[PDB]
Length: 28
Image 1 (cartoon, rainbow, N blue to C red):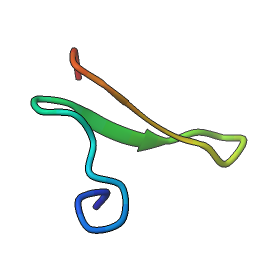
Image 2: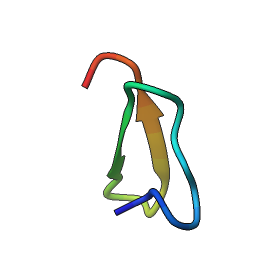
Image 3: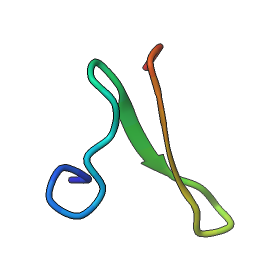
Image 4: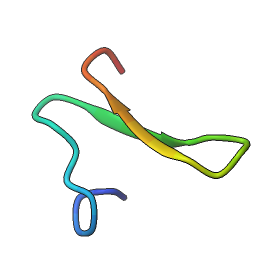
């Protein structure tokens, strides 16, 4: 998970992209 080396905003989730990027969104 991205909660030990990224810490996404409150109420947001991060997912890996087919390119190799990590981003979080407040809308799942």
